């Protein structure tokens, strides 16, 4: 009876195994754009993905992760609210059963069809495993998806999903360029928070881009053909794998722009 997104194992249950679920710095949150203070001391965000090397894509039973070879200094996030340099290890998405929901963060209560999370670890902690033991171990770039025009650079991901339909399936996934998932502007909001899945550790500097990317209805429909279950188990579509907004608890949200 492991955690999931269903009625009996979903977000409202997670606190029993992971009491930090009711902690002081839980994610996601609703971003009240009217209360985010423009911090003119925030430096330009630097997203440097030109040497990124993807390895594999995996259905982990909750989402699918595109994992990177992070053994060298190759795909780094720095600047903005961050001290030091953070290295890309994986990205994944959260999405809905319908276009009207799916994002974890919300913007003045608005939900997007999906949300991309590019997960980076603070290089001063040596690797991901030790970084998640630190309150500033991770920096996650969050990007909203809306349904409209297709995102051409997403199509390579969409096309491999049929090979990882069920929990535990993985495939080789090399030479994927995550620059093709980024919107024009790097305007963002930033706040301190957590992983949005168990173990819900409070190690994340969140950097949520204001500008969504557009994906096609057909692209997100293919996400919704994935399965939460393993092969040879009853089929449960992987949809609505998002945690809802959590209490802000007097954290503050900063803005990179006016
Ligand atoms: Zn996520």
Image (cartoon, helix red, strand yellow):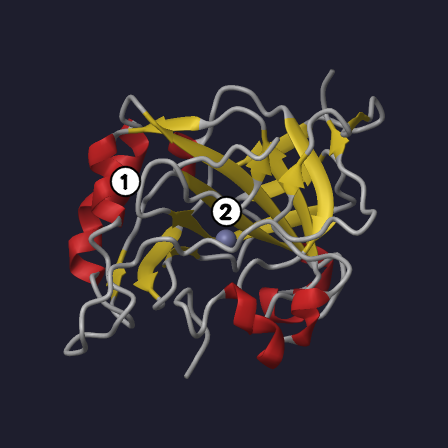
Alpha carbon distance from label 2 to label 1: 16 Å
Q: Which residue is mark 1?
A: 220
Seen at 42% across and 69% down, the residue is 4
Seen at 31% across and 41% down, the residue is 98
Front-lying residue, 2 or 199: 2
User: Among all residues in the image, which is located at the extreme top?
Assistant: 258
Residue 182, position as x, y percentages in the image: 46, 30
Q: Which residue is mark 2?
A: 117
Q: Is residue 157 above or below residue 215?
A: below
Q: Is mark 2 within 8 Å of ligand 1?
A: yes
Residue 43, position as x, y percentages in the image: 76, 28
Tell me the quadrant of the picture where the N terminus can be found.
bottom left
* Element at label 1: helix
Seen at 77% across and 29% down, the residue is 35
Reading the chain from its start, which is encountered first: label 2 or label 1?
A: 2
Q: Nearer the viewer, mark 2 or mark 1?
A: 1
């Amino acid at each position: 009876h492991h955690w999931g997104y269903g009625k009996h194992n979903g977000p409202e249950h997670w606190h029993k195994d992971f009491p930090i679920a009711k902690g002081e710095r839980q994610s996601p949150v609703d971003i009240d754009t009217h209360t985010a203070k423009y911090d003119p001391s925030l430096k330009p965000l630097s997203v440097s993905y030109d040497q990124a090397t993807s390895l594999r894509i995996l259905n982990n039973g909750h989402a699918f992760n595109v994992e990177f070879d992070d053994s060298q200094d190759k795909a780094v996030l720095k600047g903005g609210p961050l001290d030091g340099t953070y290295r890309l290890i994986q990205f994944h998405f959260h999405w809905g059963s319908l276009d009207g929901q799916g994002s974890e963060h919300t913007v003045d209560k608005k939900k997007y069809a999906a949300e991309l999370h590019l997960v980076h670890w603070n290089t001063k902690y040596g690797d991901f495993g030790k970084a998640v033991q630190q309150p500033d171990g991770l920096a996650v770039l969050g990007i909203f998806l809306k349904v409209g025009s297709a995102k051409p650079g997403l199509q390579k991901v969409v096309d491999v999903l049929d090979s990882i339909k069920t929990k535990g399936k993985s495939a080789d996934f090399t030479n994927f360029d995550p620059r093709g998932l980024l919107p024009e502007s790097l305007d963002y909001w930033t706040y301190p928070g957590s992983l949005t899945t168990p173990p819900l550790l409070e190690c994340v500097t969140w950097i949520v881009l204001k500008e969504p990317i557009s994906v096609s209805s057909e692209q997100v429909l293919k996400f919704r053909k994935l399965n939460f279950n393993g092969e040879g188990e009853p089929e449960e579509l992987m949809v609505d794998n998002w945690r809802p907004a959590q209490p802000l608890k007097n954290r503050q949200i900063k803005a990179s722009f006016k």
